[PDB]
Image (cartoon, coloured by chain):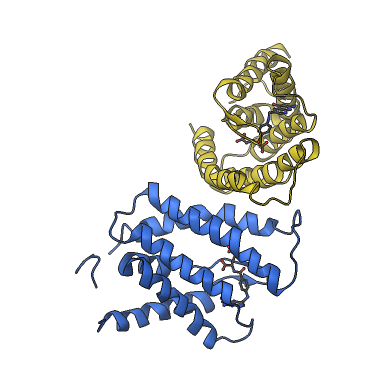
Chain colours: A yellow, B blue
Amino acid sequence: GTKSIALMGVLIAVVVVFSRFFAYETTFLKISFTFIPESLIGMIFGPFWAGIGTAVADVVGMLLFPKAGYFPGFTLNAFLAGAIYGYFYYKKEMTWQRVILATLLVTVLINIILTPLWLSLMYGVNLANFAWWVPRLIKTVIFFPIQVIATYYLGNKLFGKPL
Amino acid sequence: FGTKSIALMGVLIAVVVVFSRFFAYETTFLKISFTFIPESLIGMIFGPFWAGIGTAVADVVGMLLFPKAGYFPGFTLNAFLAGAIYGYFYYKKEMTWQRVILATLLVTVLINIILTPLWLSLMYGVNLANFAWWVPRLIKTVIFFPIQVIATYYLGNKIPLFGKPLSE
Ligand SMILES: Nc1nc(=O)c2nc(CNc3ccc(C(=O)N[C@@H](CCC(=O)O)C(=O)O)cc3)cnc2[nH]1
Ligand SMILES: Nc1nc(=O)c2nc(CNc3ccc(C(=O)N[C@@H](CCC(=O)O)C(=O)O)cc3)cnc2[nH]1
């Protein structure tokens, strides 16, 4: 489907933009707004194609802007986001309950279980430092509210040609 | 030098004990107290230092009564810190979003995550970190922190103050 493809291209483009220019990016933390386009992309296109949508959005991301370095497991992250967004959100009506438990399953399962894993995995980390976790946990706990408010709102301002 | 501070405080300590022992969720290694509401009132009423001692003793009568689960000091070290934090942010200064958040944040990080699991380390003996030994904890801290910024903020902006503020 073309129409779907145009949409996808633009959306992949926006995800790239968020991660691209307006994130807080430092060596062991990024603060971006890369959750918003991806949940719209989860809503329109559903789990598998939101998954692929965002995974390739990441790889386009690093092919363009590589200085950060490429680590495989981060693109798995992208994919999971898509699937999760899509699976919770495509396409039941947004419910505080479920903007909430999507958003939880994303924060606990990709942000504190896995991203610390990747860096640990191929950056040399003394995981043992649990003063390593303090910015990560300040953040992990501050932005969940932001994320939930924003997602709810976006969720509740026909989607397009998705599937 | 307190004639009524003692009586009313006794009453608040009692509220704390009930909220703590009678009314809230628990299992080994984790809990949701809803004692932040009365312990934050004491931040608001008593300034930091007494609120700290206030809830420290609220803990210890808490355990004079309600013996099983033993007594462990560093938990009452938590209790004094909670009191003192709510005391420092909420007494004599307006409670706004910008500061309910930074109190609830310092209690949460410094006590619920830096310190409490560190006492659970010594008593029950599981020192090591486990993905996901922690996790029910982290689930609880990240789901519930908004509940406290939305409950103590509203504690700070009320429902039917009437008589006299910030002295009583
Ligand atoms: N494939 C790949 N894509 C990337 O964009 C990438 N970027 C970096 C640059 N370094 C970083 C910096 C921060 C975080 C990080 O803390 N990520 C949080 C996201 C928080 C948010 O978006 O709000 C995470 O949990 O993943 C990861 C890698 C390194 N390898 C990569 N590898
Ligand atoms: N001194 C003392 N005070 C207590 O309140 C106490 N309570 C118990 C009962 N067992 C438990 C069970 C759970 C938690 C607990 O995890 N408390 C945490 C909840 C988690 C969090 O920090 O978010 C807390 O908030 O205090 C403490 C004691 C045993 N010894 C004590 N000893």
Count the marks.
0
Against B147, residue A83 (above or below) is above
Percent coordinates x, y for residue B163 in the rendering:
19, 69
- Residue B23 falls left or right of residue B128: left
Can you tell which quarter of the image residue B113 is in?
bottom right
Residue B35 appears in the picture as rendered:
no
Percent coordinates x, y for residue A26 in the rendering:
61, 31
Can you tell which quarter of the image residue B115 is in?
bottom right
Closest to the observer, B119 or B33: B119
Against B143, residue B122 (above or below) is below
Query: Residue, x 60% and y 65% (percent of image)?
Result: B116
- Residue B56 falls left or right of residue A128: left
Query: Residue, x 40% and y 59% (percent of image)?
Result: B152
Q: Which quadrant of the picture is home to ligand 2?
A: bottom right
Can you tell which quarter of the image residue A16 is in?
top right
Query: Residue, x 56% and y 72% (percent of image)?
Result: B75
Percent coordinates x, y for residue A85 in the rendering:
66, 36
- Residue A70 falls left or right of residue B108: right
Closest to the observer, A43 or B55: B55
* Quarter of the image where the C terminus of chain B is located: bottom left
Against B11, residue B131 (above or below) is above
Residue A44 appears in the picture as rendered:
yes
Query: Residue, x 51% and y 75% (percent of image)?
Result: B20
Percent coordinates x, y for residue B126 in the rendering:
75, 67
* Quarter of the image where the N terminus of chain B is located: bottom left
Q: Residue furthest left?
A: B163
